[PDB]
Image (tube, rainbow, N blue to C red; front, side):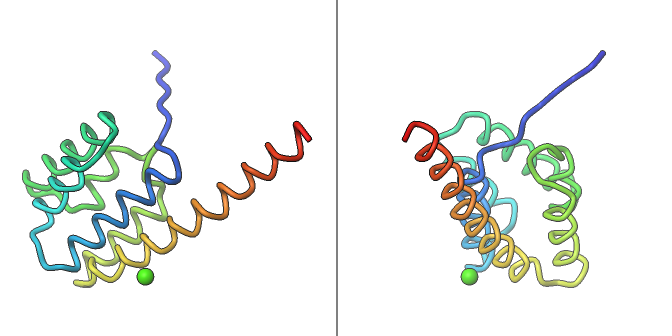
Length: 122
Ligand SMILES: [Ca+2]
């Protein structure tokens, strides 16, 4: 009974984290923010995931706890940061920090991937 799951692409994580941060900072309810990010996704799997995260949130779970249903997508640091914002009343600010982080991660990582590819078939 071995299982294996992969997360999402670094740009896909950057997009959904930016969108969530944007919506939460505009003052819309968290559950409605999760709905909009899901409904705006081009990726069926991400829609399904965020529907599922939202479903746990509506059943009373914190965002951090709900994201822990997808540990292969949101790592311990990401979830820890969310948990910190929620425990402290600064989810809005932590999501902004997570969105900036994920964006810079995507950019840096994409560069390396591209440079690797560039040099290889040179
Ligand atoms: Ca920023």
